[PDB]
Amino acid sequence: SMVMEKPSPLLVGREWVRQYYTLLNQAPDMLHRWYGKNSSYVHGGLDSNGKPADAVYGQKEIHRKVMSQNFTNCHTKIRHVDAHATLNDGVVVQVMGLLSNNNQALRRFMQTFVLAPEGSVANKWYVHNDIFRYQDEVF
Amino acid sequence: MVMEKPSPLLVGREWVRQYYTLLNQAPDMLHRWYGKNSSYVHGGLDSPADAVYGQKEIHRKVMSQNFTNCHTKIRHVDAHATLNDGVVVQVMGLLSNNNQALRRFMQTFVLAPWYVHNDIFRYQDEVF
C-alpha cells in the first residue's frame, strides 16, 4: 500500500526505451498497438538510389512496415537516453545505442521518440513519432 | 504572394541552416529562440552533462561553449509533424568548433508554432 509521486519525464522515457527494445525482440507484431493514426515511424534502410528510406503513418502502415523488417532475435545495447518534457504534456526521447538483427553484427544508431499521453486512460502513453537511423547508412 | 504553409521537412531543414549560421555569426543572439520551458544541452562530460532550462540559463551555457570557426557538415535531417502542428527534427552531422577535431553528433529539436522547445545535442565520442 504505497502512493508515490508521479513519474518524471526521464523515468517515462527510459522506461519506454526498455519496453520498446524488449518488445522488438520478444514480439514485434505487438509494437503497433502503441501507435495511433497520427503517428510517424521510420527504422533506417535505404532505397534504389542509396538515399535513406521514407517514413510511414498510422498504426496500419506502421504495423505492416514493422513486419517487413523481420525483427528476429534483436539484441540491443543502449548507451544513452535523454528524455525532456516537451509541449502538450509530451516527452521527447533521444536514444543512442547499438542494435543487431538476425544475430548479425551490432550497428550504431540514433533514435528520437515523441511520446504523448493517450488522452482517454489514466497514465497511458502512445508514440507520436519514431525516428530511427542506423549510423552506417548516413555516415 | 501567399504560399502554402511549409511541410515539416522543409521547416526543419531551413531551421537547421538558420541555426548553424547563427551558431557562427552571432551565438549571442541564439537565446532569443527559446522560452521559459525550453531545454538545451550541447554535449559535454561533467565529471553526460545535464540540461538547462529557461532562456537566461540557456544564454549562459551558450557562451560557455565559445562557438567560433564552426564548420558543420549535415549528413541527414529528419523532420516530422508532432503534437499541435509542431515539428520534431532529428539532425545527424559533423561539427568542428574553433579549429578542433570534426566530431560526429546527433541533435533533436522540437519546434513549436517558430520557437525552440527542446534542443538536445550529443557528440558520439562522449557516448560510444
Image (tube, coloured by chain):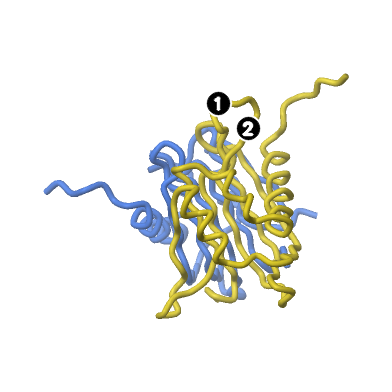
Chain colours: A yellow, B blue
Q: Is residue A20 visible?
A: yes
Discs 1, 2 touching: Cβ within 8 Å: yes
Visible in this render: residue B74? no
Q: Which chain's residue wears label 2?
A: A
Q: In which quarter of the image is the C terminus of chain A?
A: bottom right
**Residue at 72 percent of width and 48 percent of height:** A19
Say few, some or many: other residues with alpha carbon within 10 Å of mark 2 (under 14 / 14 to 19 / 20 or more): few
Distance from the alpha carbon under mark 1 to that under mark 2: 8 Å
Give the secondary structure at mark 1: loop
At which x and y percent is residue B45?
Answer: 74, 57
Residue drawn where x is 69% and y is 52% of the image: A81
Q: Which residue is drawn at 62% across and 54% down?
A: A29
Q: Where is residue B8 in the image (x, y as percent from the top left)?
A: 37, 52
In the rendered image, the quadrant that contains the N terminus of chain A is: top right
Residue highlighted by disc 1: A120
Closer to us: A33 or A75: A33
Image position, residue A83 (x, y; %)? 65, 45
Q: Mark 2 points at which residue?
A: A124
- Say whether residue A121 is left or right of residue B11: right
Q: Which amino acid does label 1 sit on?
A: Ser
Assign a secondary structure to mark 2: loop
Residue positioned most to the left:
B1
